[PDB]
Image (tube, rainbow, N blue to C red; front, side, top):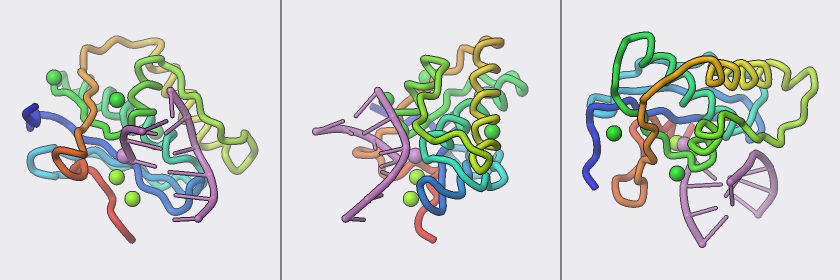
Length: 136
RNA sequence: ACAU
DNA sequence: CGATGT
Ligand SMILES: [Cl-]
Ligand SMILES: [Cl-]
Ligand SMILES: [Cl-]
Ligand SMILES: [Li+]
Ligand SMILES: [Mg+2]
Ligand SMILES: [Mg+2]
């Protein structure tokens, strides 16, 4: 398995889980940050991974790009394939923002088409995904 | 068990 | 050590 360098890599980072969630997408080859979401006060790791992939799909579609997306999240790759994010996070006023984003991301997937391959980054062979946040 |  | 997920 060769890395597909002509691709977009996404990943989540957080302070607490559940906690403050952010995510970003980078050029897999150069590491250039192509988008980064403003921190969301309360969410889960998997919600952030999910939003990161969907944002990537929207980013590539808008730019007429056929590049694949790498994610390291087994969970979020499945959620995108299903068009359904099966998060356990409670719905309350503190989690309303992220739940609105998740609901809207599902809605986008149910109203648009894409051919973008969503690929599992093979961390065991390649090391950390290039969008990883690391340690604070 | 696997993945974050 | 615990949390989010299949
Ligand atoms: Cl978002
Ligand atoms: Cl997977
Ligand atoms: Cl591909
Ligand atoms: Li990740
Ligand atoms: Mg990471
Ligand atoms: Mg980390």
